[PDB]
Image (cartoon, rainbow, N blue to C red; front, side):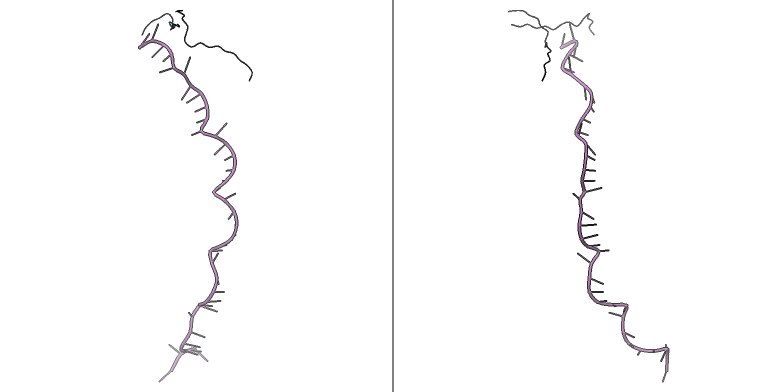
Length: 33
RNA sequence: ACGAGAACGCAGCACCAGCUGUCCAACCUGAAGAAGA
């Protein structure tokens, strides 16, 4: 029942350097066998 | 005072011998813990 323009993010803090990173990142790479 | 009387259709003998209730077959198909706590 709450109206919002967009789905706000949920960043974090890493130890200090206040770096905001979205929880759950990864990379994709493909190699034979 | 009978075409009569007397006379066990009876004795011995395994419904038995051989024979896989077996053969093939996936408990399998399709489906985020997100979301304003």
